[PDB]
Amino acid sequence: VQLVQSGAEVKKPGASVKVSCKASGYTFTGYYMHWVRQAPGQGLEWMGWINPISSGTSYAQTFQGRVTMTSDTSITTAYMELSRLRSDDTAVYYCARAAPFYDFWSGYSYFDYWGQGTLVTV
Amino acid sequence: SVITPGTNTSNQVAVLYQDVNCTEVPNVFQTRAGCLIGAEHVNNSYECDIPIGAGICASYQQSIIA
Amino acid sequence: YELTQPPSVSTARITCGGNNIERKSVHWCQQKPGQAPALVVYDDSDRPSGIPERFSGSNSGNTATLTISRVEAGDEADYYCQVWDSGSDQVIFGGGTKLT
Amino acid sequence: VQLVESGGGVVQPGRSLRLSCAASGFTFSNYGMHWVRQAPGKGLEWVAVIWYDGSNKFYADSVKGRFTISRDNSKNSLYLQMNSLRAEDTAVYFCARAFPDSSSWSGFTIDYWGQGTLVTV
Amino acid sequence: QCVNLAYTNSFTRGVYYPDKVFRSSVLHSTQDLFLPFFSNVTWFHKRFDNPVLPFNDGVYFASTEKSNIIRGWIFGTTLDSKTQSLLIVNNATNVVIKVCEFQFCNDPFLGVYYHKNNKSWMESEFRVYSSANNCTFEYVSQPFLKNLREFVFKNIDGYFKIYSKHTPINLVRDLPQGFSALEPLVDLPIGINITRFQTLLALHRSYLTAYYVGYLQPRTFLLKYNENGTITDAVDCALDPLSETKCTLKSFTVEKGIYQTSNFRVQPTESIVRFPNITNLCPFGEVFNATRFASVYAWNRKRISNCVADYSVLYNSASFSTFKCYGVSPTKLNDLCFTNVYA
Amino acid sequence: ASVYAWNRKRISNCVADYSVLYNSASFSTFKCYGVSPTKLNDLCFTNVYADSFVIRGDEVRQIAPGQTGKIADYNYKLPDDFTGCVIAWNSNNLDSKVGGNYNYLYRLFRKSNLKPFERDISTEIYQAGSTPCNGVEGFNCYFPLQSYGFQPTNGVGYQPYRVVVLSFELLHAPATVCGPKKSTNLVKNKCVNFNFNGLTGTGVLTESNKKFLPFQQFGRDIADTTDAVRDPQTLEILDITPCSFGGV
Ligand SMILES: *[C@@H]1O[C@H](CO[C@@H]2O[C@@H](C)[C@@H](O)[C@@H](O)[C@@H]2O)[C@@H](O[C@@H]2O[C@H](CO)[C@@H](O[C@@H]3O[C@H](CO)[C@@H](O)[C@H](O)[C@@H]3O)[C@H](O)[C@H]2NC(C)=O)[C@H](O)[C@H]1NC(C)=O
Ligand SMILES: *[C@@H]1O[C@H](CO)[C@@H](O)[C@H](O)[C@H]1NC(C)=O
Ligand SMILES: *[C@@H]1O[C@H](CO)[C@@H](O)[C@H](O)[C@H]1NC(C)=O
Ligand SMILES: *[C@@H]1O[C@H](CO)[C@@H](O)[C@H](O)[C@H]1NC(C)=O
Ligand SMILES: *[C@@H]1O[C@H](CO)[C@@H](O)[C@H](O)[C@H]1NC(C)=O
Ligand SMILES: *[C@@H]1O[C@H](CO)[C@@H](O)[C@H](O)[C@H]1NC(C)=O
Ligand SMILES: *[C@@H]1O[C@H](CO)[C@@H](O)[C@H](O)[C@H]1NC(C)=O
Ligand SMILES: *[C@@H]1O[C@H](CO)[C@@H](O)[C@H](O)[C@H]1NC(C)=O
Ligand SMILES: *[C@@H]1O[C@H](CO)[C@@H](O)[C@H](O)[C@H]1NC(C)=O
Ligand SMILES: *[C@@H]1O[C@H](CO)[C@@H](O)[C@H](O)[C@H]1NC(C)=O
Ligand SMILES: *[C@@H]1O[C@H](CO)[C@@H](O)[C@H](O)[C@H]1NC(C)=O
Ligand SMILES: *[C@@H]1O[C@H](CO)[C@@H](O)[C@H](O)[C@H]1NC(C)=O
């Protein structure tokens, strides 16, 4: 299982950033793709997830209304677009894999695979 | 069971609900054979025509009587 | 569906072409300068009351004609060809033919 | 049989205008009605027809979705509501009394025309 | 384009040849969808009213006219472009039967007029639908529309089956008495979902300036075939106790006597469910999500008792590759009680 | 098609040569139910349905009568009285792409099992718990479909297989699909074997005087056995009697 994210981005306040995450080594649609933010000197914050099979999403209240998650199964890639960027959106953004909610053994409760973080500076 | 004169005579019938109470089924005559509906019970005794049971017979006399 | 008729005609005969126009009823109205149009011929060759017997017409094949015999100076008007298009529920007008 | 148009005038593109026509001399409720427009220097172009009971409204392709034809039998009057007018809609608008077309189930030709009212956009 | 626009006795009508087998001089008992004898048939007719009716399990349709007003029918569900619908239309030379994603008008019809008032030349405006996309079936054959015209419409086993009969009658306000069997007209290999239908009428313009509908039911009929294999009579076995007797005796005549024809049985009106009033769930998860499993030679046995067992949680799980039940159905487990469960 | 949205092709009014399929080396599965694969060319059917879809190798066994599992239960169900043939072959060279083919879907969750030949292509969110989902997936609210994600490097059980199911319709109706079996001359007034459009038997054929209606293909006596047939080529009505016999 590999998760490969796009390179670092530098944006201005009010701009939007779209971070990609290319998945391989597993059935793409069999897992949820989560995004987790890590601001410098801070801990990990969950942003939301997308379910590639349905393109269904759920967002953390913190980012709801600013973050849009999409995916394209033909290239097994997930995307996270964070709009109206603020200076405090400077962070390393990770994509992470977790089981879907129908997983019997609660594999959805945790993130078993992470990509290399993508740094976005605002 | 359906009690009838031949269709060569009449299309009237009477129906016997065998060993059934006339209060359970739905000229209503309760006999030991069951509940006989559609036949008019009379006191006049005749030779047996169509046997019902327990001494009761029915005949076509027009309407079906017991 | 569209009608085709000449810009002007100098017995005057005004032609109105179309695709198998024979199957459609052709009606004609006359518009004098500064005035509203008025019905002259309907259902190919029938006239409404008030229209002189000079006005006649026909409808055959791919063309219809309004024929005006004994043409008068009072007939110097724009004559329009129209049909009902049952395929689109529209009234279709031609360009209009001016008499001189 | 007479028809009188009113409600014309001058408007700018994007704005609306309502026209009306008063009918008299005949039983309005027994006839369908047409609107026809004539741009300066051009021939007649059909706009819309409405059935005598107001149940069926048909429009020319060029006005469909913008213009609404309606009638009020109680007031013996015909209306045309023109929304989102464009420069191309400049024309004299006429109301007219419909006449049955023998080559169609419910088709119409035009019998009586009003004098018309000028609309400039 | 689209243009905006009582009960009678069925007697013994609505009987048709149930199959394509020749029989003669015989009484044959058959179970099929028939119009019940002496049933309530709805009678349909300035104003216009031509409503969409339910199809239910099948339809009996009849009309009496010399004006050929009834031209066809629409069958389907939504009767719009969302689903496949069946359109049957008859004209002077042919009948056209199509199945398409039709977008039907609220008041579909054929507008009849005389072409330029030529009474020897009739024409019609086809105003039934605005679109007919993605047609899956098309069939064209000979047209079948005082003169009483009867039809039976069945939608079953992948076929839309039409039966018909055309006879003269001496009444207008009702259906005739007597018996006449309808013969199969066409079996259409369509296989679509039909819940509603409506009649297509031919309307002269001057009309705006009747037919009967019954429903078929699963009934047992005794059909009498004559020497020429024609059905000449029938008994609706559930009509009354006499008809029941006739069917029991396989005869259209009954001798004087008493006959056992059926059984009387009071039916239950409620369902009473009484289970132990416990709420604690059975510890199945503790078996399935154990950190360690035993070796098969030394397998573990967990005894489960005195609890509520929801097996649909396990069965409806996507996480199991094998789920095989023996001596019991996996979908009936939640309705069963056991003295014990071993895991 | 995806197995959840399988395709149904209706076959009629034609000559069906099934030995071309059966004698092919290209199929891995060819299982017939209610009929022998070597007798198919001698049979006539009123209709033949060809249902086609893709499933993974391990699931091919579910395409049979009396089977259970996600495919048998939620996608493609065969009846226990199924008459027909299930034909499958490995399509790894067609239906698998590097990185995964996510075009082929199957239904993973459903409120109840499908009826035979029922086709469910809805995508309504599945309620696993007691709380209404309101169209929003999440905890105890699942998207009912899932992809196979076929890849060329998968083990055989996870490779795509193309499945064609031929259901044979045998109704008391005119047969429209018959094998390549050639016809012979019609012989009457003799004791012969016969086969009329799939209807076999032994007896003596004679001209009938029975008043068959245009739609009737054969007749039966009071014993409910065939005693007359309509010849499928001449439309002649023939009476059938048994060949003379008796006790000795
Ligand atoms: C191993 O499994 C047990 C049992 O859980 C049952 O089986 C699981 C596979 C799932 O199907 C569960 O949904 C099912 O109940 C787990 O213990 C149980 O965990 C659940 C989920 O957290 C608990 O339910 C919650 O209980 C709290 C009250 O404490 C409520 O407020 C919540 O709304 C919810 O109902 C359940 O009570 C708990 N039962 C017991 C006896 O502990 C166990 O955690 C699991 N272990 C692992 C590693 O997965
Ligand atoms: C039936 O009734 C007729 C008179 O209508 C009678 O002649 C005949 O003998 C009767 N047959 C039987 C079996 O009762
Ligand atoms: C029928 O039921 C009534 C009570 O409703 C009872 O009085 C009567 O004796 C019963 N008759 C028979 C024959 O059971
Ligand atoms: C039969 O006699 C009884 C008296 O025992 C009486 O009540 C009943 O009404 C009589 N029935 C008839 C038909 O006369
Ligand atoms: C028919 O009625 C509907 C609803 O009022 C209307 O939208 C539609 O335009 C009408 N059809 C015609 C031709 O006017
Ligand atoms: C249907 O007709 C029958 C037979 O005359 C009658 O009993 C019944 O009341 C009628 N139903 C309605 C709704 O009129
Ligand atoms: C037919 O369509 C209706 C919707 O109009 C639906 O409720 C019904 O379940 C469908 N029946 C079948 C067999 O598809
Ligand atoms: C009847 O329908 C068929 C098929 O659409 C067409 O070919 C035929 O010309 C039609 N006949 C008439 C009189 O419209
Ligand atoms: C009426 O139509 C028929 C058939 O096309 C034609 O032969 C006849 O000449 C027509 N008559 C008139 C007056 O148009
Ligand atoms: C007809 O089928 C095509 C696919 O073959 C589809 O794209 C189109 O939308 C369908 N037409 C309608 C009205 O849905
Ligand atoms: C049966 O057909 C014959 C002709 O062979 C005819 O004479 C007889 O009347 C028919 N039977 C009936 C009931 O019509
Ligand atoms: C073919 O069969 C048809 C009946 O289906 C028959 O009418 C036709 O004459 C036959 N042709 C030959 C060459 O046998």
Image (cartoon, coloured by chain):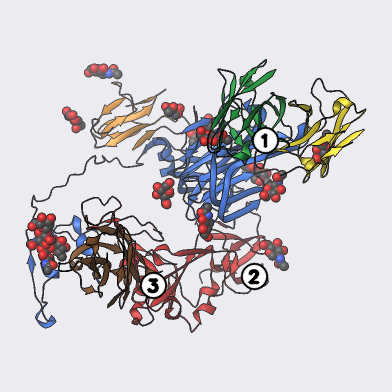
Chain colours: A brown, B orange, C yellow, D green, E blue, F red
Quickly name the residue at label 3: A75
Local secondary structure at mark 2: loop
Of all chains, the one bearing label 1 is: D
Kindly indicate whether the residue at mark 1 contacts the one at mark 2 (C-beta within 8 angstroms). no
Report the number of numbered marks.
3
Kindly indicate whether the residue at mark 3 contacts the one at mark 2 (C-beta within 8 angstroms). no
Of all chains, the one bearing label 2 is: F
Q: Quadrant of the N terminus of chain F?
A: bottom left
Q: State how far apart marks 1 and 3 are (Cα).
A: 54 Å
Q: For residue F30, what is the image quadrant?
A: bottom left
Q: For residue F118, what is the image quadrant?
A: bottom left
Q: Give the left or right position of residue C94, taking residue E147 as reference.
A: right
Quickly name the residue at label 2: F190
- Please state the quadrant of the image where ligand 5 appears: top right
What amino acid is at disc 2? Lys
Residue A44 place in picture, x, y as percent:
17, 66
Quickly name the residue at label 1: D46
Residue at far bottom of view: F25
